[PDB]
Image (tube, rainbow over all chains, first blue to last red):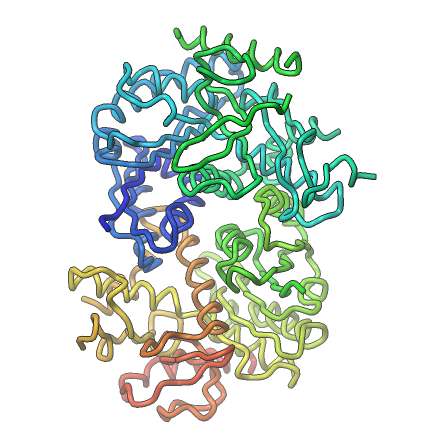
Length: 313
Length: 306
């Protein structure tokens, strides 16, 4: 019954602000499970992190055993079982995707080295910050074989939850009845949102519906148009869902989208990528669900291969 | 059907922290669907549409519906719970009388709207400052349609801060600490009291609790949001679900018939137990300690035009 150590990077940012109270209240590891939060951000953010820590204290969360704030990944990751990687170099005006990938490669190499050096052997990692799939690949490869490749993932669950919700609104049904949308491929505009296997209760969703891909791909930009700011609440909620389903299991009959290491996948997607697939999770482990498709994936595969080359990988 | 919950100030930072907690079940529990009705000023309507979109994108199974509006009557239509985070923005070197009058405008209109269209048994907590006096304005402006026992002001953030500070000073987990009391006004005259506090089964503090909000602003450059949202959830949750045996929590409540000789006609923070949506003041936990906070609440009542 020792507290489970959970690291959150980018912890002075808006996703981190929305995420840490969910972890502390028990949404991640369960309502009985004590947690320790290890919060990482850049050195100029130390005072802001102290502010986050002070607010966490002021919540009087019964499960939150300890909070540590740091700018050193070797401190943040020390003994951690779960690492939620929100920190990343943000896209500035004038950057192409390649520029963003190159700014992020240094971050994720340092973090992957640190995780391999000091985290628990079985540490499970999810990358939220963009470009998420490639950042996760960089992280994994920087561990030089010391990190289980099945334990490094990238988050497509915000896109998945966006698609569940959209399908529910289009069908006029409660979102609680909708399952088994699939986001394939990259967490980018080449993602393939797929409703062909989706159901409402057990009814194929098509049979219940009397722009979908564009709306899902464009939703982040829509949030920015409305709010002036990127999604934070919903991203934090998705990161909790990604991890919670991974650790606790997906319920019977449900699969969820996860960016996972592609070696040995049942779809013939190239090896050596972090690629979003439909997954069940049982006993802390993902399994890709087969039979749900292939030419549909060519563009997102090609983009992931291009990014991997750009990563010097 | 879904319990209808209004949140005012819904385009602000407390609102942003609060609405996903409500939507995920933290307010009313794991089986109770909710409908959120989000109110802010008209210039904030686009921002509110962004909050609604993010709520949709969470795919919350308990969130049956979201409405966003700048019209209080639309926000409060049929609502059973109203969490009032919106208040007048406090200006640089503004007179306290002026601030109270400007808040009186807001809370009078909102109280009238609640009276007009909310459910008869609607429960209200005011978060936005000055919380106690704003709550009193709201109640008095409802001209009888609101049960006085159903209008409250939040001191739970101060209470949670005191629990945490006591646990830190004693070097124990905060889960072991209970029964701090915040008496009086949600202001610098609050009386943080540890005389009745328990650690387990076993029986600078004041300045630190009173100064905590300013400390957060120094560190973050912004007022508390996460912690205030969490406290709002705790205040309503404990009110509706009930407080566990042996636990009391601080709540600003209407002061008629209190057992402490505090004057009537105020919203005043007391130690309370709750059962099934009703608070009861816990007696015997003190009186001259309260004189200054009493006097400040009476002054604010008069300055508000009440």
